[PDB]
Image: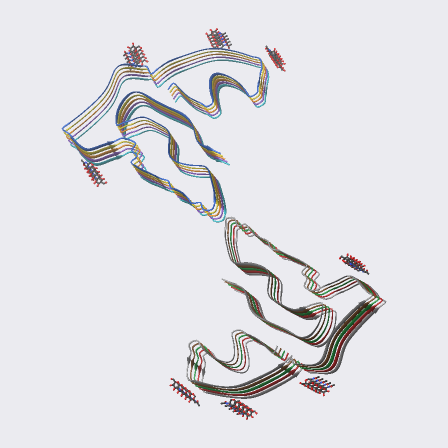
Chain colours: A red, B green, C brown, F blue, G yellow, H orange, I purple, J cyan
């Protein structure tokens, strides 16, 4: 990635900022700018490319062959019992929360068993994350 | 990705900002700008490319062959019992929440068993995330 | 992706902003701008490309062969009992919510068993996400 | 994707903004602009391309062969009992909600068993998401 | 990655900042700037490349062969019981929360069993993370 | 009064009481009784008795002469307000009574201004008094 | 008063009491009784008795002469307000009573201003008094 | 008063009491009784008795002469306010009573201003008094 | 008073008491009794008795003459306020009572201003007094 | 008073008491009793008795003459406020009582201003007094 940028407030080439009650007198500004950008990226010079896979099985016997891919959850138990037995009292509950499984951003490209891959793969994630604000 | 950008408030090439009760006197501004951008990206020079897969099975016997792909949940149990037995009291509940499974952004490109892939894959995710604000 | 941009408030090439009770006197502005952008992207020079798959089975016997693709949920149980037995009391419930399974944005391109793919795949997701605001 | 943009409030090439009770005196503005954009994208130079798949089965016997594609839910149970037995009390419920399965945007391109694909696939999702606002 | 940048507040080439009630007298500014950037990246000069895999099994017998990919959860139990038995007292709960499994950003490129990969893979993650602010 | 008697249960001269499952064998009872009572009471031996009253008023003047006998109530106020404002409750009232002025036995012989009395006056009061029994 | 008697249970001259499962064998009872009572009471031997009252008023003037006998109540105020404002509660009232002025036995012989009395006056009061029994 | 008697349970001249499961064998009882009572009481031997009162008023003037007999109540105030404001509670009231003015036995013989009395006056009061029994 | 008697349980001349499971064998009882009582009481031997009162007023003037007999209450105030403000509690009231003015036995013979009395006056009061028994 | 007696349980001339499971064998009882009582009391031997009172007022002036008999209450104030403000507690009140003015036995013979009395006056009071018993 030639250019990746996280700029919180302001991004600019040339910035003239006059802010919060200043007195701005005689000014002359002369800006002479020549800018050239030439981008050649991911150009590929390739005569011949071969992707070839071959499998042969003969005079063979297979019984109870098991291939199980990734990300198996099987047996997972979430038990979160909450019991409140307020008899004769005062209870104030403000900004109270319970969360079990929260997934914001899930990015998954390739999960397989057998893979032949020729090329380019790029993942870019940018975020501002504020979970809980109260009061 | 040639250009990826997270600019919180303002993005500009040339910015003249006069803000919050300033006094802006005699100014002359002369801007002379020449800008050239030439973009050649992902150009590919390819004579011959072959993707070929072959399978042959002969004089073979297969029994109880099991292939199970990824992301298997099988047995998952969520038990969240809540019991409130307020008898003779005062209870104020403001900004209270329960969430079990929350998925905001799920991006998945390729899940398989056998894959031959020639090319380019790009995933870009940008977000501002504020979950809970109260009060 | 040549240009991907997250600009919170304002994006502009040349910006003259006069805001919040300023006094704007004698100004002369001369802007002379020449801009050229030439975009050649994803051009491909390809003489011959072959995608070929062949399978032959002979003198073979197959019994109980099982292929199960990805994303199998099987057995999932959500139990969320809520019991409220307010007898002689005061209960105020404001901004209270329960959510089990919430999916905002799901993007899935390709899930298979056997795939041969030649080309380009691009996924871009941009969002501003505010879940709960109350009070 | 040459240009993808998330601009919250305002996007413009040249912006003259006079806002909130300013006094705007003698100004002369001269803007001389020449802009050329040439877009050649996804041009493909291809002489011969062949997509060919062949299967032959002979002198073979198959019994109980099972292929099951992805996204199988099988057995899923949602039990959310709510019982309220208010006897002699005061209950105020404002901004209260229960949601089990909410799907806003689901985008799925290709799910199969066997796929040969030549070409280009692009998915772009942009949204502003505010779930619950009350009070 | 030629350029990766985390700029908290402001990024600019030339910045003239007049802020917080200054008095700005006679100034003349002359800026003469010529800037050229030429980017050739990821260009590859390749005559012939071959990716080839072959497997043959003959006169062999296989029984109870088990291959299980990564990320197996098997048996996981979350037990978080909470019981409150307030009898005749005063309880104020403000900014109280319980969270079991929270995943913000998960990026996974390739998990497999057998993989042959020719190319380039890039992952960039930038975020500002504030979890809980209250009071 | 020669004989005044309060005998709660039984009064008798000679009492043979066989009670509550006794065995009463050979008995011979011989009772020889001689009883003489001679009553001379309130015999009066009187030759001459004179009751004489005389009043004479002469050459006299009387104005605003006021004689007021006994037992004057004049101004008496009984105020017993009872207000019951049962809103949403349970009230059981069993054996509840209000009494202001209760007079059981009033015996008055002589009230006068001027009295001359020769003789005998006797008042005898006997009672069993149980006011309130409940439950 | 020659004989005044308060005998709670039993009064008798000769009492043979066989009670509560006794065995009463050979008995011979011989009772020989001679009883003489001679009562001479209140016999009076009187030759001459004179009751004489005389009043004479002459050459006299009387104005605003006031004679007021006994037992004057004039101004008496009984204020017994009872207010019950049971809102949301449980009240059980069993054996509850309010009494202001209760007079059981009032015996008054002579109230006057001027009295001449020759003779005998006797008052006898006998009672068993149980006011409130409950439960 | 020759004989005044308070006998709680039993009064008798000769008492043979066989009680509570005794065995009563050979008995012979011989009772020989002679009893003489002679009562001469209140016999009076009187030749001459004179009761004489005389009043004479002459050449006299009387103005604002006030004679007020005994037992004057004038101004008496009974204020017994009772207020019960049970909100959300439990109140059990058993055997509860309020009494202001209770008079059981009032015996008054003579109240006057001027009295001449010749004779005999006797007052006898006998009672068993139990006010409140509960439970 | 020749005979005044307070006998709690039993009064008798001759008492044979066989009580609580005794064995009563051979007995012979011979009782020989002679009893004589002669009562001469209050006999009076009187020849001449004179009760004489005389008043004369002459050439006299009387103004504002005030004679007020005994037992004057004038101004008496009873204030007994009771306020119970049970909010959210438990109150059990058993055997609770309030009494202001209770008079059981009032015996008054003579109250006057001027009294001449010849004779005999006797007052006898006997009682068993139990006020409050509960539980 | 010749005979005044307080006998708690039993009074008798001759008492044979067989009580609480005794064995009573051969007994012979011979009782020979002669009893004589002669009562001469309050006999009076009187020839001549004179009660005489005389008042004369002449040539006299009386103004504001005030005679006030005994037992004057004038101004008496009873203030007994009771306030109970039980909020959220437990109060058990058993055997609780308030009494202000309790008079059991009042015996008054003579109150006057001027009294001439010839004779005999006797007052006898006997009681068993138990006020409060509980529990
Ligand atoms: C600069 O500004 C001042 C303002 O007081 C003005 O008098 C003066 O002429 C200006 N000079 C130039 C060169 O513009
Ligand atoms: C502006 O820049 C160009 C760049 O080649 C130059 O030729 C020209 O003379 C400059 N003019 C001024 C006024 O600076
Ligand atoms: C690569 O591209 C050039 C033109 O840019 C062409 O002359 C050349 O033949 C291409 N390569 C092959 C192997 O054909
Ligand atoms: C395959 O698994 C089953 C049960 O898991 C088992 O009974 C069987 O014997 C296995 N296969 C072989 C060839 O052992
Ligand atoms: C600058 O502004 C001032 C304002 O006071 C004016 O008098 C003066 O003429 C201006 N000068 C020029 C060169 O514009
Ligand atoms: C503006 O820039 C161009 C760039 O070639 C230059 O030729 C020209 O002289 C400049 N003019 C001025 C007034 O700066
Ligand atoms: C590549 O493109 C050029 C023209 O840009 C063409 O002359 C050449 O023949 C192409 N390559 C092949 C292998 O044909
Ligand atoms: C396949 O599985 C079943 C049950 O899981 C089992 O009974 C059978 O024996 C297995 N196949 C072989 C060839 O063992
Ligand atoms: C600048 O503005 C002022 C306003 O006070 C004016 O008097 C003056 O003539 C202006 N100068 C020019 C050069 O426009
Ligand atoms: C404007 O820019 C062009 C760019 O070639 C230049 O030729 C011309 O002289 C410029 N004119 C002015 C007034 O700056
Ligand atoms: C590629 O395109 C050019 C024209 O742009 C053409 O002359 C050439 O023949 C093409 N390539 C092939 C292999 O034909
Ligand atoms: C296939 O599965 C069934 C039940 O799961 C089993 O009974 C059978 O034996 C299996 N096939 C073979 C060839 O074992
Ligand atoms: C600038 O504006 C002012 C307003 O006060 C005016 O007097 C003056 O003539 C103007 N100057 C020009 C050059 O327009
Ligand atoms: C405007 O720009 C063009 C660009 O070629 C230039 O030729 C021309 O001279 C410019 N005119 C002015 C007045 O700036
Ligand atoms: C296919 O499945 C059925 C039931 O699942 C089973 O009875 C049968 O045996 C299986 N086929 C073979 C060839 O075993
Ligand atoms: C600088 O500013 C002052 C303002 O007081 C002005 O008098 C003076 O003429 C200015 N000088 C120049 C060279 O602009
Ligand atoms: C501006 O920079 C260019 C760069 O080549 C130069 O030729 C020109 O003379 C410069 N002009 C000025 C006024 O500095
Ligand atoms: C590498 O690229 C050059 C041109 O930049 C080309 O002449 C040369 O043939 C390429 N290498 C091979 C092995 O073809
Ligand atoms: C590489 O590209 C050049 C043109 O840039 C071309 O002449 C050459 O033939 C290419 N390489 C091969 C091996 O063809
Ligand atoms: C495969 O596993 C099963 C159970 O796990 C077992 O009974 C069987 O014997 C295994 N296979 C062999 C060949 O042992
Ligand atoms: C007394 O009674 C008994 C009863 O058993 C009897 O046998 C006996 O004859 C009796 N005796 C007399 C004297 O009556
Ligand atoms: C009974 O009593 C009288 C009394 O005088 C007597 O004369 C008589 O003899 C008695 N008789 C018996 C059998 O006791
Ligand atoms: C009698 O009473 C009245 C009013 O009470 C009064 O006006 C009058 O004067 C009185 N009599 C005399 C003689 O004063
Ligand atoms: C007394 O009683 C008994 C009873 O057993 C009897 O046998 C006996 O004869 C009796 N004797 C007389 C004298 O009555
Ligand atoms: C009974 O009593 C009288 C009394 O005078 C006596 O004369 C008689 O003899 C007695 N008789 C007996 C049997 O006791
Ligand atoms: C009294 O009574 C007797 C008779 O009992 C009688 O002879 C006598 O005369 C009486 N007294 C007078 C004074 O007469
Ligand atoms: C009698 O009373 C009245 C009012 O109470 C009063 O006015 C009057 O003067 C009184 N009599 C005399 C003689 O004063
Ligand atoms: C007394 O009683 C007994 C009872 O056992 C009896 O045998 C006996 O004869 C009795 N004797 C007399 C004298 O009555
Ligand atoms: C009974 O008593 C009287 C009394 O006088 C006597 O004369 C008699 O003899 C007695 N008799 C007996 C049997 O005791
Ligand atoms: C008293 O009574 C007797 C008779 O009992 C009688 O003879 C006598 O005369 C009486 N007294 C007078 C004074 O008469
Ligand atoms: C009697 O009383 C009244 C009022 O109480 C008073 O006015 C009057 O003067 C009194 N009598 C005399 C004679 O003073
Ligand atoms: C006394 O009693 C006994 C009872 O055992 C009896 O045998 C005996 O005869 C009795 N004696 C007399 C004198 O009664
Ligand atoms: C009984 O008593 C009297 C009293 O006088 C006597 O004369 C008699 O003899 C007595 N008799 C006996 C049996 O004791
Ligand atoms: C008293 O009484 C006797 C008789 O009991 C009588 O003779 C006598 O005369 C009486 N007294 C007078 C004074 O008369
Ligand atoms: C009697 O009382 C009244 C008021 O109490 C008073 O005014 C009056 O003067 C009194 N009498 C005399 C004679 O003073
Ligand atoms: C006394 O009693 C006994 C009882 O055992 C009896 O045997 C005996 O005869 C009795 N004696 C007399 C004198 O009664
Ligand atoms: C009883 O007592 C009297 C008293 O006088 C006497 O004469 C008699 O003899 C006594 N008798 C006996 C049996 O004791
Ligand atoms: C006293 O009493 C006696 C008789 O008991 C009598 O004779 C006598 O006269 C009395 N006294 C006077 C003074 O009379
Ligand atoms: C007293 O009483 C006696 C008789 O008991 C009588 O004779 C006598 O006369 C009385 N006294 C007077 C003074 O009369
Ligand atoms: C009597 O009392 C009253 C008020 O108490 C007073 O005014 C008056 O003067 C008194 N009498 C005399 C004679 O003073």
Figure quadrant of residue A129: bottom right
Classify residue C113 as left or right of residue J36.
right
Name the foreground residue: B80 vs C110: C110
**What is the quadrant of residue I80 in the picture?**
top left
**Would residue J53 be found to the left or right of residue I101 on screen?**
left
| Left or right: residue C55 compared with residue C32 | right
Q: Is residue J95 visible?
A: no
Above or below, A93 against H117 in this view is below
Indicate which quadrant contains ligand 32. Answer: top right
Q: Nearer the viewer, residue A117 or G114?
A: A117
Is residue G95 visible from the viewing direction of this image? yes
- Whole-percent x, y for residue A123 in the image: 65, 74
Q: What x and y, as percent, mark residue A34?
A: 56, 88
Left or right relative to B117: residue I99: left
Instruction: In the rendered view, tell whether residue I11 sits above or below residue C131.
Output: above
- Number of numbered labels in the structure image: 0
Quarter of the figure with the N terminus of chain C:
bottom right
Estimate the x, y position of residue H64 in percent, counting from the top left. Answer: 20, 35
Image location of residue C4, percent across then percent down: 59, 76
- Comparing F126 with J119, the one in front is F126
């Amino acid at each position: 990635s030639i250019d990746v940028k996280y700029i919180g407030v302001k991004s600019a080439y040339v910035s003239y900022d006059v802010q919060k009650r200043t007195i701005y007198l005689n000014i002359t500004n002369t800006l002479n700018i020549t800018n050239n950008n030439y981008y050649s990226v991911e150009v590929e010079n390739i005569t011949a490319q071969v992707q070839f896979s071959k499998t042969v099985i003969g005079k063979a016997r297979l019984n109870n062959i098991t291939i199980i891919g990734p990300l198996d959850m099987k047996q997972i138990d979430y038990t979160v019992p909450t019991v409140i037995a307020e008899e004769m009292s005062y209870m104030y509950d403000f900004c109270t929360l319970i969360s079990i499984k929260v997934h914001n951003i899930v990015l998954m490209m390739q999960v397989t068993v057998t893979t032949t891959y020729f090329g380019h793969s790029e993942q870019i994630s940018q975020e501002r994350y504020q979970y809980v604000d109260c009061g």
